[PDB]
Length: 166
Ligand SMILES: NC(=O)C1=CN([C@@H]2O[C@H](COP(=O)(O)OP(=O)(O)OC[C@H]3O[C@@H](n4cnc5c(N)ncnc54)[C@H](OP(=O)(O)O)[C@@H]3O)[C@@H](O)[C@H]2O)C=CC1
Ligand SMILES: CCc1nc(N)nc(N)c1C#CCc1cc(OC)ccc1OC
Image (cartoon, rainbow, N blue to C red; front, side, top):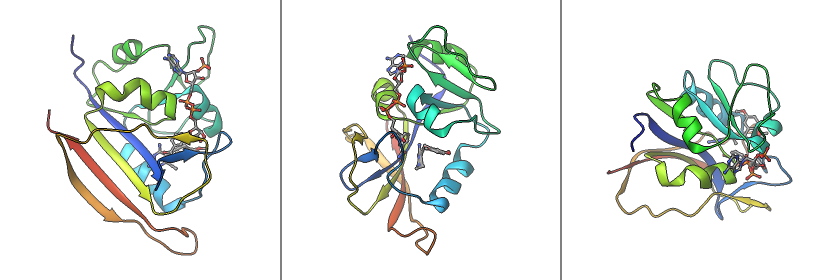
């Protein structure tokens, strides 16, 4: 029944798991976006249809895969899938794919996540979209580092990476 690729989550959330507000990001952290680009470069990005449209354009140097239940949905420079299994088919030969949100898409792929790249922002934003709860039993933190806080990046935040022990 198994897929061969590593399923990694890529997400940034606040102290209460908020990841979005009014179909956008509640914060603006250029430095954190650089870490995201650095980490995901050359790997497929899997994104919910809403997430993708908020971004608005294909992210260069990565396979953009959009998840939608719309069978007539198309976008140039991007791939479209309509299910977890169709993603696994498209990415069958990939080493590692990144589930890039948003919340519905995180929920979809949660039974399959092997590795978690999560930025935690030490602030409580007003929001309406939340990262799903996770049982970390049998996971281990393998990297942690404080983010750069300066004029362009006005919050305290940390990068964490957790690996499943399965
Ligand atoms: N801080 C962070 O790291 C991140 C924050 N965000 C934020 O999250 C928000 C977006 O999240 P959310 O509203 O949940 O939207 P999603 O990105 O999860 O997209 C939801 C869409 O995905 C498609 N979809 C959902 N379930 C399925 C399924 N089972 N099969 C096929 N397609 C499916 C549907 O598309 P369709 O309607 O076309 O059928 C649905 O409308 C935005 O605010 C964004 O800015 C997003 C990513 C990361
Ligand atoms: C907040 C940026 C971010 N960080 C982490 N660690 N994981 C994520 N999935 C995201 C995200 C996002 C959405 C987004 C991305 C983007 O360029 C990559 C541009 C705009 C975006 O939302 C409008």
